[PDB]
Length: 145
Length: 97
Length: 48
Length: 48
Ligand SMILES: *[C@@H]1O[C@H](CO)[C@@H](O)[C@H](O)[C@H]1NC(C)=O
Ligand SMILES: *[C@@H]1O[C@H](CO)[C@@H](O)[C@H](O)[C@H]1NC(C)=O
Ligand SMILES: *[C@@H]1O[C@H](CO)[C@@H](O)[C@H](O)[C@H]1NC(C)=O
Image (cartoon, rainbow over all chains, first blue to last red; front, side, top):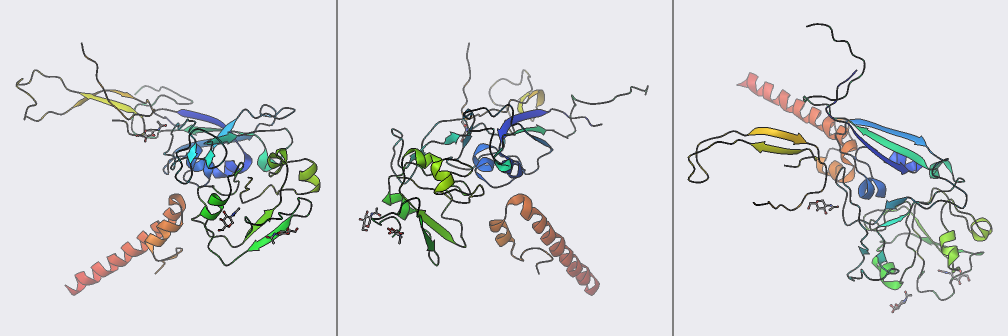
């Protein structure tokens, strides 16, 4: 029974503890390098476990998450990039191994993990409740003015 | 002293060293070993110098190459089941060089 | 401007005195409010 | 006076906890400090 100016749907698969992590202004590598919500967030976050589409025999290492970022992540930012994180002072950028680490690591999932390590599927609905022409409603009646 | 040792114990008998009453500067580990697996779970590898820890355990044991990837929370294998099993709620980092 | 995405464009067109950037006050009428929501850092314009 | 919050130092609260959790504590501090200032102002009005 509300009217919203514009609705944004953001979708990604994240682990069970990360559901507790994902919330307006929290701590953790996912919350600060992978996805950050605004402090005054107005919306809903939807989480349900998906162990039938993100799991298969011999595992599935298709998904990804970032742990190495130069700074914190501004809210709603697509910082998609493959740049080696610098450690110490070496300009590396040429070879893996010591003090040259990849910004993201495989998000491998198998059908046999713990509940905190299960493939949860998360989508977040963001709404804009402001005095502006809306686009989305629900039930309606149009009684004459 | 845990990185400059010469007889790192085997995985079956993993020496557990208790670290207390010290300032945990991580540059000393950064400069000592050319790592190949610095995966962190409970904390950020960049963010280690700004957190105060009640107690730190340093369990050191030399192991094979694939066993480096074997050793992780929620894992399995001949080492992960009979030699050393990492807890699922592991708040810490591993270092492999 | 690009505050929280939502690109905004402002315009008011008038055959003003025509010397140059003038003095008299003039408000700006919005034309399009569009939620782009992408990364933005540099600016350039296209000529004829 | 902590006024019912974690600590009486706003800067300590800021540097110790995250924004959306220290928000309640700093709001408590505001409600305490402003109300105290209100009492001071009213008493000053009576004395004046
Ligand atoms: C987004 O734009 C800001 C503004 O300069 C920039 O600092 C940041 O690197 C950009 N993020 C990208 C391109 O992923
Ligand atoms: C051991 O200590 C010596 C003396 O400081 C140092 O030169 C060497 O790099 C250290 N080696 C390791 C593996 O820590
Ligand atoms: C741990 O015990 C093993 C036992 O062989 C030893 O070789 C190693 O030096 C010990 N590490 C210490 C005391 O830091």
